[PDB]
Image (tube, helix red, strand yellow):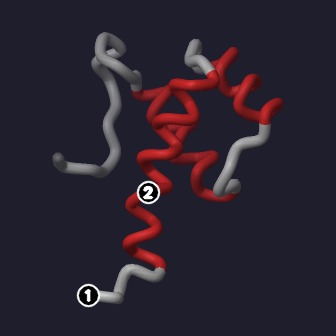
Amino acid sequence: SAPGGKSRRRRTAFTSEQLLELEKEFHCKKYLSLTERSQIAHALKLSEVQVKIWFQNRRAKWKRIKAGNVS
């Protein structure tokens, strides 16, 4: 896949807004808390699992960046 920004559509798994707010709060917090995740779910019409899974995917690649110069 080709990571980066992504906006418009409003008709697939995530919108502009959904994708924007997500890369926002994965910048500062490495892990959303219970309340933060629930809050973001209300705004973004997502659910705590969907938010967890997006954030988990973003967080995984970071592990092979941060310390992954072991190959």
Q: Which of 49 and 9 is in front in this view?
A: 49
Residue 43 at what x, y percent from top left? 66, 18
The residue tagged with tag 2: helix, strand or loop? helix
Where's the C terminus, which quadrant?
Answer: bottom left
CA distance separating discs 1 and 2: 17 Å
Residue matched to label 1: 71
Give the vertical position of 25 relative to 49 (above or below): below
**Which one is earlier in the sequence, the residue at label 1 or at label 2?**
2
Amino acid type assigned to the residue bearing label 1 in the image: Ser
Q: Which residue is drawn at 40% across and 22% down?
A: 15
Amino acid type assigned to the residue bearing label 2 in the image: Ala
Q: Residue 60 carries which label?
A: 2
Q: Residue at x 59, y 57 (%)?
A: 27
Q: Residue at x 47, y 37 (%)?
A: 54
The residue tagged with tag 1: helix, strand or loop? loop
Give the vertical position of 60 relative to 32 (above or below): below
Total label count?
A: 2
Residue 69 at what x, y percent from top left? 35, 87
